[PDB]
Length: 48
Image 1 (tube, rainbow, N blue to C red):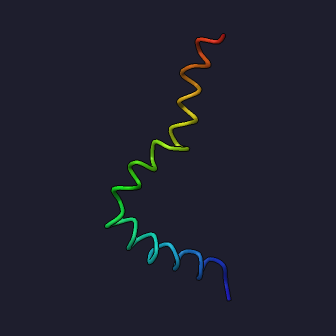
Image 2: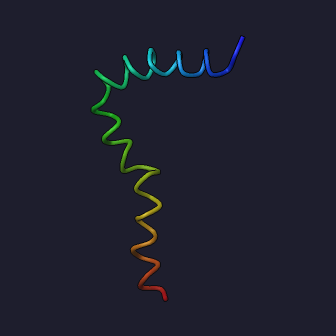
């Protein structure tokens, strides 16, 4: 019972299967938290 055997196996199936036909979400999920970081970095430059 390894975490890598259940963790990677869970991704390639739930993520690999859902992320594929659901990849369209990943796009809208790529600018979320991933875009919130760089989003503040752009505004922070004006604050300084």
